[PDB]
Image (cartoon, rainbow over all chains, first blue to last red; front, side, top):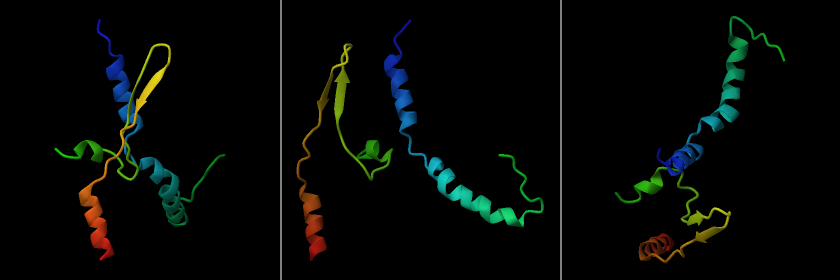
Length: 49
Length: 49
């Protein structure tokens, strides 16, 4: 019954421009951590392409 | 509050501007000219000394 375009767009913009550094962590540091502990596991990795 | 609106984000790349858009798609922009600041200039002067 009321226009929500202005408020809907504002909320979406804030989520798009949030200062999260998880994406840069997953791309750079997470692979290194997984590679380091991999040879030490009791159950060695088992993967499919 | 002073500068709190700006610290809710990454301050390494800051700028200020505003715009609005018509229904046919035209846009109008306002980019204010940054004036000088005596305090920042004095701080740099102390750095040289």
